[PDB]
Image 1: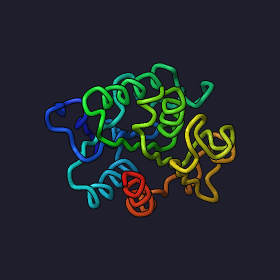
Image 2: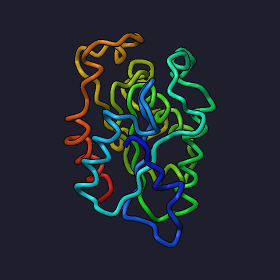
Image 3: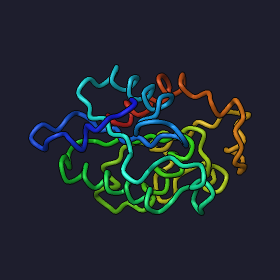
Image 4: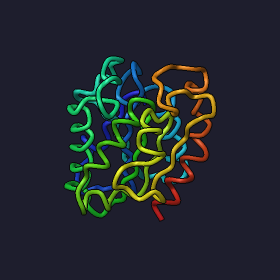
Length: 191
C-alpha cells in the first residue's frame, strides 16, 4: 500500500510465484488503502518473496453510497475486479492467484469471484475477507466458490457481519489478523 499495480505493469515474461489482488474499504485512499491491504501484502511477502501486488482501482472509488446497492457494491466495481482476475489469467495462467478484501472491498471481491468462469476461477487458490458486509446474506462464504479456499474474518462486535451497515470499533481492527493468520492461510493455499 497505498498504491500497488504489480499486475497491471508486470510483464508476462517475468511472471512471479504468486499474485495478490486486493479490494480496499470504503473511503480508504489509493487502491490498497492503509490498514488491512498493506498489512496483508506485507505478511504474504514475508512468506513468498517474488509476488505481484494489485489494488482494485479504476472505477472503484470506495464511495459510501455504493454500499447500499444490492450485493454491497456497484456492478462497475465488480466488473473491474473481474477484469483483473482475467488479466492475471492472460498474463500468467500458471501462476497461482490469491485475493483479499476489506469491508466494501470484501463485498466486491466476493461478488467478482462468484461470477468467474472455469479456468480463471480455478487459478484463484484462496480468498481472505475482513469485516465482510455480505456475511449474513451469503451465509459466511462466497457463492460458487469452495468453502475450503475461503477464510472470513468477522470480529465479534462487528455489526456489518450480522447484516447491518454500521461501523463499530470492532470493524476497525483487522490488521493483526491480516498480517498474521490470513497471510499464513493464503500461503498454505498456494501449496
